[PDB]
Length: 263
Ligand SMILES: [Ca+2]
Ligand SMILES: [Xe]
Image 1 (cartoon, rainbow, N blue to C red):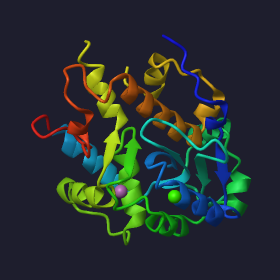
Image 2: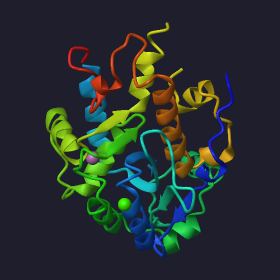
Image 3: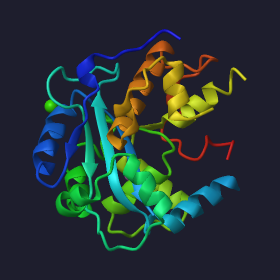
């Protein structure tokens, strides 16, 4: 597979804590009109379609975000030559909340998580959601959201963006999601149906096939949003946004739980 190496400065992730939360959102705010494609990734500490939704609904208000990544670029994957284009928001964490197993906590450790920094400089999730609401990224179809295994990320996003009044059924959940993100794609789904037309579906195997080096920055939460966006824009470019049968990717815009008829 030909090597795909994006310009070096595209592979930089700016860490965000309570100290630079507002200034970073000020930068996001002025870049979005041009770099209108936004990818998101998350890290939580803690019919088949109706099962997935019910499993998610029963878990969202008990799952607490520790990290969240956002990456911005235009439709062709171009990014600003100066300054950060990917952010890793680190949220506040309570050193005494007895909500985890040592397997998970030790797992997180390796993943590059300093709990002490989260306890003393972690950002407040409500403050973050408020900044996200007014950033210009929500409720605007000129902005395209990119996700991988949406359901849970969006579930969470919607959960914080709203009055914690989570919807009560799949149908109403989808309604709210389309209202906050009128233009979005689940890259995992786009790839699954592509890599199902020629016959793994992980972001990693997708990135390999596109020939993206296994840079370690890609292993962090911020790096993940970055890998996601790079992959979306490249896969899209090589495919002139078409599926192996000529169909346009748009056919799957807004699809979380499967296209109408395959649910
Ligand atoms: Ca602007
Ligand atoms: Xe959302």
